[PDB]
Image (cartoon, rainbow, N blue to C red; front, side, top):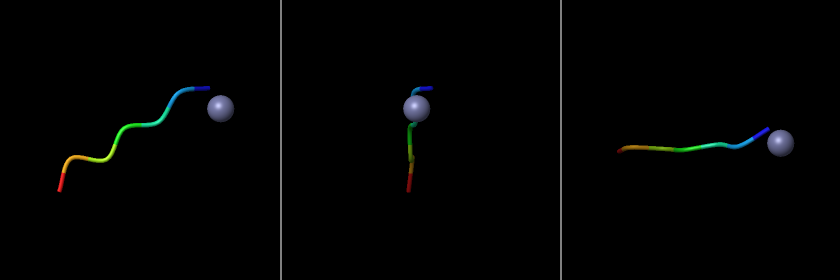
Length: 7
Ligand SMILES: [Zn+2]
């Protein structure tokens, strides 16, 4: 799957 991190 795809992964996104929004700090
Ligand atoms: Zn993946």
